[PDB]
Length: 176
Length: 61
Ligand SMILES: O=C(O)c1ccccc1NC(=O)N1CCC(c2ccccc2C(F)(F)F)CC1
Ligand SMILES: [Zn+2]
Ligand SMILES: [Zn+2]
Ligand SMILES: [Zn+2]
Image (cartoon, rainbow over all chains, first blue to last red; front, side, top):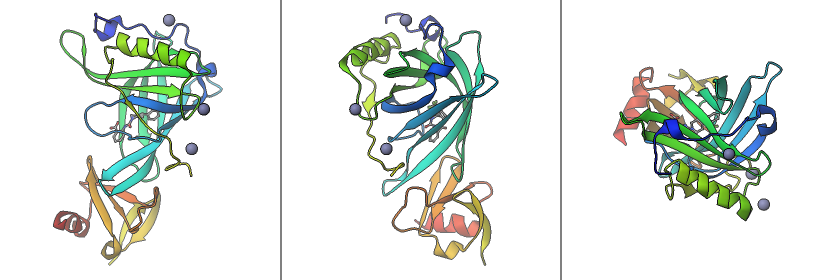
């Protein structure tokens, strides 16, 4: 928790792409600088015959104070020496035109209840992160059991993001 | 009169006259016919490729 260099962060041991697959609901988020999905954020992870992992991400986007839309993005993950650290190329589909390439770290998960994700986009010279985003994912769209909640809080502190997350809803805006 | 623009991911003939919502978002301009703002009812074009009549509508605010 006191060493805040991105290099010193533990990630998920022996991360298993296949057990991670399926639907993950974002329950809380820590925003990066700039534009970002707002809420109703749902990610679907998949593993193909090759073992290459993929995901879709859907959520609400606020174009104007009076104009909310939904946006879909697809991401393709390139493996690293670390089974939990990926490089994710992503792009919007249909008429969502945002795209990019981010580090994508699975900081921890039990695959059945919760996951903590993390992406440092820009590092300070001293190795701490100057621009990051992070999701708390749950298999349950509405909440986490208290056991999971305790672990998540620990991981947020380890990321030096304690108290920097916002809870985000799932109210059907993009899936009904 | 109309312009070739992508709308809900499909190439459409868009009458810019009838656009009721327009916004700059990142490097792109998003637009919709719909006053009700249906969640997926929108198209988009890059700022650099945007027809001038669309930019005019955007900038008049
Ligand atoms: O990145 C931008 O420039 C941007 C601009 C406007 C609006 C949203 C934006 N970006 C995001 O919201 N996100 C969160 C989702 C993330 C993604 C995409 C596809 C598959 C999985 C994931 C995963 F990382 F969440 F798993 C991509 C970055
Ligand atoms: Zn551990
Ligand atoms: Zn529940
Ligand atoms: Zn739903």
